[PDB]
Length: 282
Image (spheres, one colour):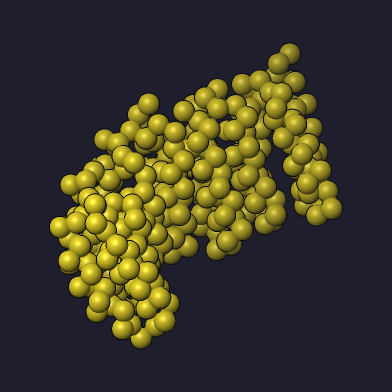
């Protein structure tokens, strides 16, 4: 009775998902799919997700771009009633972090924001972050650059950020910054820039350690990692400057050197940061 309804649901969904391939029908098709998603049982949800997870797999770009968006769109329509699926959902977005396609990457980040804001205190935040760390541990660049961007988007969107679980994170970030086989330092630096702006993510006692870590990447030989390092320093200035006044002399000294950098984008970045660290009073 219900089970044959689900087969008929699948049929209706598949019928629309094929309209995502043709480009003139693409938005008709998403609109249809969002309408299908608005009226849906628990079991209809699970079926719908299923369909998204399969069509996710590796066959055309616009299609999996849009299936990733709809994982997001689901979350924002149903909130908590969709909560126990969160792990399969996260797992299925992280899987696509591997594609060296920035359209997919953008979709993946965006959806993770939506998930984080829409769905569900406590170790809800665990179910989002563990997969990203496992991703950052894997040795691919495309993957760890993207997991870095998701990690940022997630922390600034998460509705109820358990600080305890979030504060056990800074140790592993330090470790990834220290290692010289970490392939994504520039993006991970960016993420630190966001994380210090997010109340409750970095305990004040870990800020100084992390400032060291960041300031050391002004000596990296990837110029994009040095640029990112300056930028992260600017972020810590306007965000937590006054928390770090003791270290101010240090940072300005570092940057007074770094501003002579061979590479204009590094100079330009170091310049903004220097002015900002010079601007702290409070």
